[PDB]
Image (cartoon, rainbow, N blue to C red):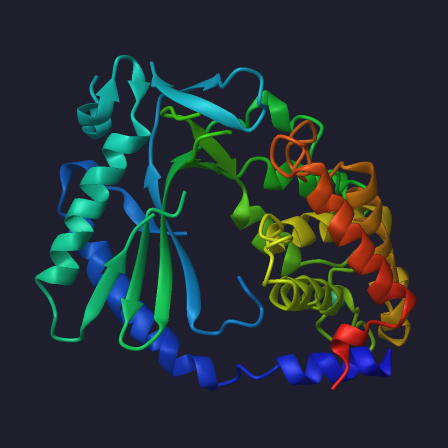
Amino acid sequence: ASKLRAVLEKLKLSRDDISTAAGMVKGVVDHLLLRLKCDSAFRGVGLLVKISAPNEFDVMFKLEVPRIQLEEYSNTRAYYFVKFKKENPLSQFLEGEILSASKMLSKFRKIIKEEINDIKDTDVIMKRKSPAVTLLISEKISVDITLALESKSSWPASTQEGLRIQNWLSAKVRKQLRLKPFYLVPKHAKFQEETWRLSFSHIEKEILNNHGKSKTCCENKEEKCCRKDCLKLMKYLLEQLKERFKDKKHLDKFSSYHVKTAFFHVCTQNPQDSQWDRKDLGLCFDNCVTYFLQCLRTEKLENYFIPEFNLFSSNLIDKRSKEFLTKQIEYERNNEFPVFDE
Ligand SMILES: [Zn+2]
């Protein structure tokens, strides 16, 4: 538990170190952003992870899309086709009544390829593989560019029982959050079609930076909880294990989003700030680790917003993999986390 504090001190090294990198990234983003704003398809475009990879950045480009009509993809409660109900500037991407993910991405990558290949004053390169574009700025400054539509409709029905923050952040807060927009990113489910996936990364960001039962948690010396610290330690636990077990790729399917999702559920389970006292760091981390093991072992990790979307289903992550991680995390917990030693 003082070992855990030692780990957190080791991780805290961003202060002004990243501030130059960010400047590099912010410089290339805004130029890109204002070129897209030229295009008819990209009028409403504007801005909207790995705790130990300070040169890798993640940016989402949001695009306002009214009149929107969702159609669920074959009862996979998180993936949808996009339809409409005048004529939108996005009507150039229709493939039938369905909005084409692939076709909007090609134009998007085409236009970005223009602004990088035509402006090589400060050099840039663009690699490609939902994240449609990755850019290399100079030596290993990478930034991931994601396209998302913004919808201001009510959230889809699949989220009705999600975001179970009532006893933690209040029913009032749930109500306000759900009046905010939701987002859709092009991604296909496991087969290829023009399907989109729900994204709530902005709500996630908001509850994390306003995370207490108390409105003044994080704002005075008397109300310092260890919530963010437990999330960081959980993300580091996974990154270290993925790195150490990399020779055989047992853990390639697991990601920080799985650990962030489990963390939010423990917040729901543990709603009082007194359950996250800093003097109980060791115990709060163990509650996080213990719930993650339960997810692994039961093979159930509900998306925090979409409770019938199981991140740990066998269609996404096979059984052997989840059993292998279970065993390694069990070993770490039962030995006071040797992976954190110096
Ligand atoms: Zn706090």
Is 256 left or right of 270, judged from the image as shown?
left
Residue drawn 14% across the image and 58% down it = 115
Quadrant in which the N terminus appears: bottom right
Rendered-image quadrant of the C terminus: bottom right
For image coordinates 71% across by 79% down, the residue present is 8
Query: Is 164 on the left-hand or right-hand side of 48?
Result: right
Q: Position of residue 275 (x, y in %)?
A: 89, 61
Q: Is residue 286 visible?
A: yes
Judged from the image, the quadrant occupied by ligand 1 is: bottom right
Residue extending farthest front: 248
Of residue 262 and residue 320, the one placed in the foreground of this image is: 320
Res 286 → quadrant:
bottom right
Residue 49, percent from left and from top: 53, 61
- In the picture provided, is 276 more to the left or to the right than 249? right
Q: Nearer the viewer, residue 114 or 172?
A: 114
5 lies above or below 179: below
Q: Is residue 32 above or below residue 107?
A: below
Can you see residue 37? no
Residue 45 drawn at (x, y percent): 28, 46
**Residue appearing at x 68%, y 53% in the figure:** 259
Where on the picture, by quarter, is residue 307?
top right
For the point 22% across and 46% down, which residue is it?
Answer: 109
